[PDB]
Amino acid sequence: PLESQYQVGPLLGSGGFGSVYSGIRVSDNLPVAIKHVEKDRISDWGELPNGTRVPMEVVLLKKVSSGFSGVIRLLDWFERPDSFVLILERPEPVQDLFDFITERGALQEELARSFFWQVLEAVRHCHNCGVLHRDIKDENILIDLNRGELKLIDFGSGALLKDTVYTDFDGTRVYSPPEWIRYHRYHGRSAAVWSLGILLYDMVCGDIPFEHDEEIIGGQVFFRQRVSSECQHLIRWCLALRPSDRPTFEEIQNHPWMQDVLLPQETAEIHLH
Amino acid sequence: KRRRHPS
Ligand SMILES: O=Cc1c[nH]c2c1ccc1c3ccccc3[nH]c12
């Protein structure tokens, strides 16, 4: 029984991913987000262990939802006649990283470092669980403003992680790597690193570096804000034009710019309260 | 000039 169990509040957002609403779980008042996707729009499907045929996104979310992490967890789901309904966690209070950067401008490096580290941890988690997100971007990161914790949202463009080439992509073009732009081909991890490159520049400069395909394939990174040499170096490495010249996640997390990261609590205290 | 970009 879906409507007896959740109390539906206001629409939080809508778009390519469908329509997401605020909610409270009637039993114990847990805040939730309720996401509706129309069956006619899911072109990628999987099978649960439980026989039943679900949208890939449900598969992906159950793979990454066990235990704690920086991924918004799937708490429950339902099939309706023309849609699927996904019950997700909702942090309170929350703001997404896109609105946060619009409001605050380029972030101080200490803050960019804490945020970026937490995203790295969350993306490593997805890969450990066999899941490739494929739409890493500020708009897909929620900030718990009290705990200082970042959470990944929206696996609807995701895929099972593989080591062979991907030749399909429905994520965000301005975060897509140049081998996708020119050849309609990419490998998972290395495309993931490129999009993290775009995300890191976004954070330290106040907006993404590239809007057009020619800029993406140009691989010229101009800095519009004062950014430290070490940080510019990490960004440029993540945005290397050849995939194999990009850093591994290990290499990113061992980069000198990534040393002495703040704890989430510290980050909330210094930068968010 | 700053904006969201859909999937
Ligand atoms: O999954 C796609 C989403 C698009 N906006 C979302 C999505 C998922 C969860 C949330 C969410 C959770 C708590 C607060 C605002 C939110 N916005 C969204």
Image (tube, coloured by chain):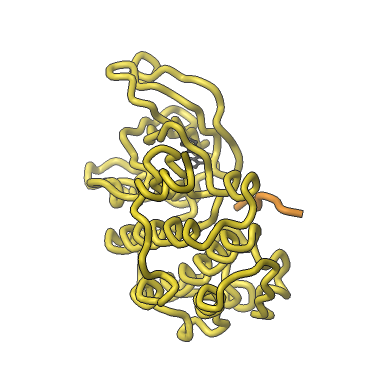
> Where is residue A141 shown, x and y percent of the image?
48, 49
In this rendering, is residue A2 above or below A151?
above
> Where is residue A187 shown, x and y percent of the image?
45, 74
Q: Quadrant of residue A40?
A: top right
Q: Given the current orientation, which residue lies at the most extreme right position? A: B1
Is residue A81 visible in the rendered structure shown here?
yes
Question: Image check: A36 left or right of A4?
Answer: right
Colour in which chain A is shown? yellow
> Where is residue A102 shown, x and y percent of the image?
65, 48
Question: Image check: A124 left or right of A115?
Answer: left
Q: Residue at x 35, y 69 (%)?
A: A162
Question: Image check: A226 left or right of A34?
Answer: right
Q: Residue at x 67, y 80 (%)?
A: A220
Q: Residue at x 70, y 68 (%)?
A: A224
Q: How many marks?
A: 0
The one of A216 and A109 positioned closer to us in this rendering:
A109
Colour in which chain B is shown? orange
